[PDB]
Image 1: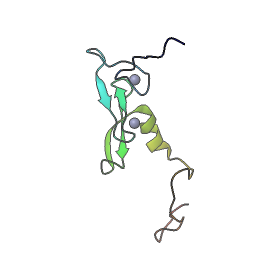
Image 2 (image 1 turned 90 degrees about the vertical axis):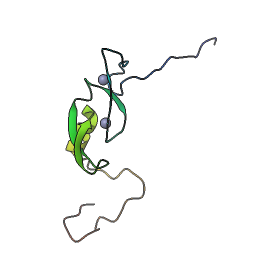
Image 3 (image 1 turned 45 degrees about the vertical axis):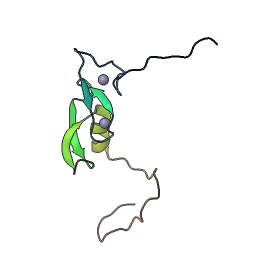
Length: 88
Ligand SMILES: [Zn+2]
Ligand SMILES: [Zn+2]
């Protein structure tokens, strides 16, 4: 009732760790979020940096290597785009 002011500062988007002299702050390329050297210790081709193996966060590093198999997103193109194995 008489409270509601949290002090959320620059933290990690993986462990929620606060960036300090000891814990430096890192940035992702794929998701584009803030991570700690600990979490941001992976590299994977990012379709944003021209498909270059940039330092990405664990998640992304896995998401880019997992290759989702769904179509949950804004208007999607027709399974058949260009003459090829183009999947749905
Ligand atoms: Zn972290
Ligand atoms: Zn990321």
